[PDB]
Amino acid sequence: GNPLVYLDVDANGKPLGRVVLELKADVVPKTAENFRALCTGEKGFGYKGSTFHRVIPSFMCQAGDFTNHNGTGGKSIYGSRFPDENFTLKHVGPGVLSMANAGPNTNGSQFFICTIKTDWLDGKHVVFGHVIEGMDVVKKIESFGSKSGRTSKKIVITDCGQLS
């Protein structure tokens, strides 16, 4: 079935808890597989050790720049970037998991979890999953953000992987 993956997140090396995500491989298989493998680290790189570097309250928590740790980097398992698979899933509310990008057909590894309905991002960002458990952890992450996206603590994905 659809993969279940997890992110264990700390704030300054203190655990916040676990976010479990369902990846909608039934709808966006290529995008789901990219994220799944970056969670396991099975290609030799991925999310473990990377940070939620851009967190904006009442908007979203963005992570996944595991190369540059600032929003300029990341890589897909396929290559530097891969195309927008489809825009079938929409930014319907909090808990939506979606790909960050630098314009059309530039998906890499950066992703975000919405904390509100971000419907102005429909048709530009590929939605590929949602939070199954740990929205309380997402709200903890959000509380360390700011209007500019700067975080007041270092929010690290200290472990991540696949549950099923």
Image (tube, rainbow, N blue to C red):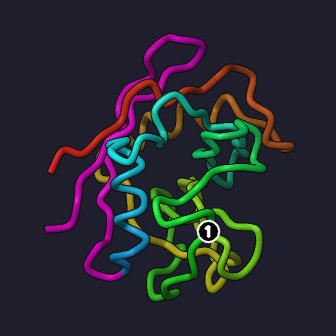
Q: Nearer the viewer, residue 43 or 58?
A: 43
Q: Quadrant of residue 155?
A: top right
Q: Nearer the viewer, residue 77 or 126?
A: 77
Secondary structure, magenta segment, majority class:
strand
Q: Disc 1 marks which residue?
A: 81
Alpha-carbon neighbours of circle 1 within 10 Å: few (<14), some, or many (≥20)?
A: some
Residue located 38% across and 79% down the image: 28
x, y percent for residue 52: 62, 37
x, y percent for residue 86: 49, 88
* Residue 25 sits inside the magenta stretch: yes
Tag 1, which secondary structure?
loop
x, y percent for residue 146: 79, 37
Residue located 56% across and 82% down the image: 84
* Residue 121 sits inside the magenta stretch: no
Residue located 38% across and 48% down the image: 43
Q: Nearer the viewer, residue 157 or 37?
A: 37
Query: Could you tell me which quadrant the N terminus lies in?
Result: bottom left
Image: 130 above or below 142: below
Q: Which residues are magenta?
A: 1-27
The reply to whether residue 111 is visible in this rendering is no
The reply to whether residue 22 is visible in this rendering is yes
